[PDB]
Image (cartoon, grey):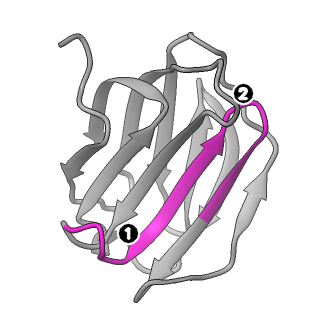
Amino acid sequence: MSSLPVPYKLPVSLSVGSCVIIKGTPIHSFINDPQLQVDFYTDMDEDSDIAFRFRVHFGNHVVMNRREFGIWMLEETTDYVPFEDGKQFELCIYVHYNEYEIKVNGIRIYGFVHRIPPSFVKMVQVSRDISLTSVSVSN
């Protein structure tokens, strides 16, 4: 009705200089472990490989990783999660030559180095405890 379906699946093509921009609001903030998850898949089904998972545990930390043939690789984390309950955020994932740069409301919180070329990404999925207003792939 007023927001996009969650979970949300968007076919994409990424190249160096692309930015994936996600606008949404954390909801259900009264539950014990509210989350946001963004997955960059290499094909259209959810069994396919994941070049980059960005999984926020709101108020706690972010965990990032990559999945190949069902197997998760080296996990990376940061406790810098500057989201606000019930306030709209702008989540920007910039595709650089060497990494995905993740900004929350204009502020860099992490850089995840590519394990496979970002041109291999075919779908972005957004899931868990957000209301989703828009997803864009810019440039």
> In this rendering, would 103 be left or right of 59?
left
Q: Image check: 131 left or right of 29?
A: left
Residue beneath label 1, please?
A: 118
Q: Which quarter of the figure has residue 43?
A: bottom left
Could you tell me residue 111's position as x and y percent? 65, 56
Q: Residue at x 54, y 20 (%)?
A: 28
Numbered label tally: 2
Q: Quadrant of the C terminus?
A: top left
Q: Is residue 101 visible?
A: yes
Residue 82 falls in which quadrant of the image?
Answer: top right
**Local crowd at mark 2 within 10 Å, few (<14), some, or many (≥20)?**
some
- Label 1, residues with CA under 10 Å away: few <14, some 14-19, many ≥20: many
Q: Main secondary structure of the magenta part?
A: strand
Residues 92 and 4: in front is 4
* Residue 112 percent coordinates (x, y): 62, 63
The residue that disc 2 covers is 82
- Asked whether the viewer can see residue 139, the reply is no
Q: Amino acid at mark 1?
A: Pro
